[PDB]
Amino acid sequence: DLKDPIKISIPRYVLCGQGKDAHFEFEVKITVLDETWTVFRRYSRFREMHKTLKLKYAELAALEFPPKKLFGNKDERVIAERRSHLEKYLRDFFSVMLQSATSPLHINKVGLTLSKHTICEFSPFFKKGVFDYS
Image 1: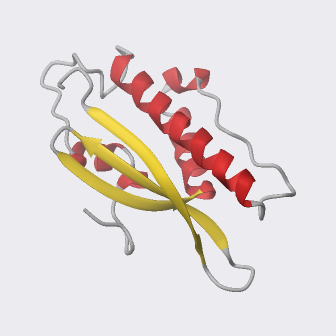
Image 2: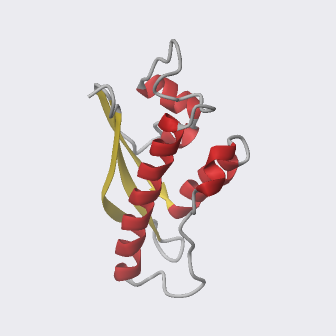
Image 3: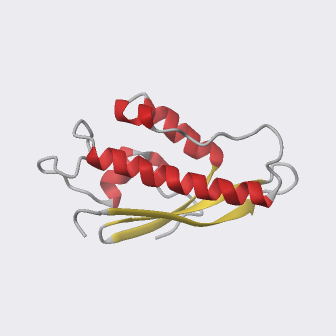
């Protein structure tokens, strides 16, 4: 309960945009303790998060971010595998950030408060934009 405070899943993906602005976005469902919310994020956004946070926190050097091949990303099977790898990435991301003692989210940091608020402050990837919902 308090030892597993952040849960995360990507139950589905959705095709957004029309023409060949058309791209997949992943439905990220996140629960921190009591609070649950959902954001839609394209692969680009996950990668930008990883890059940004990997230089701020060293414990994230051990994390391997899933690559994207140049061709073949219109195949739904590729996208489905991506959903899985991105969900595993997010789950490893939180494992590291909660268990690394050097981390601002270390479960045992004194006075650590954990909420949607502190998570959204920690990374704006998780901040709700226009299609996102609680």
